[PDB]
Length: 46
Length: 49
Ligand SMILES: *[C@@H]1O[C@H](CO)[C@@H](O)[C@H](O)[C@H]1NC(C)=O
Image (cartoon, rainbow over all chains, first blue to last red; front, top):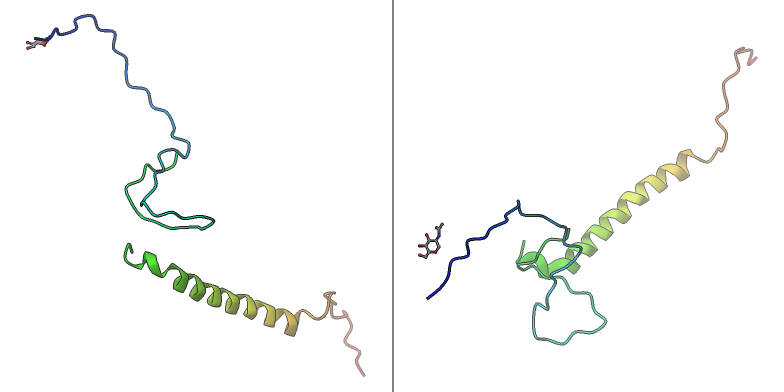
């Protein structure tokens, strides 16, 4: 069984800026001192 | 476009060659016409004998 919270203090959702965050390794291949271009599902900058 | 992403080197060299040609045209015009560094004005009087 669960209890539904009754006390509520709600405000509009705030928004902030993602400063070049959310980059992940696109593959499991080691790469060093190289500049690689890839298209994928990325979080756009800012 | 996603397929063409692996021919970036080919496109980069193509654009490099074309940019070189484009700069070369302006260079050619400069060498031919911009030899004189001062814009001399024709005299008001045309007493050229
Ligand atoms: C809270 O959760 C219960 C679970 O069924 C639900 O019945 C109830 O409607 C919820 N409270 C409100 C105000 O909807």
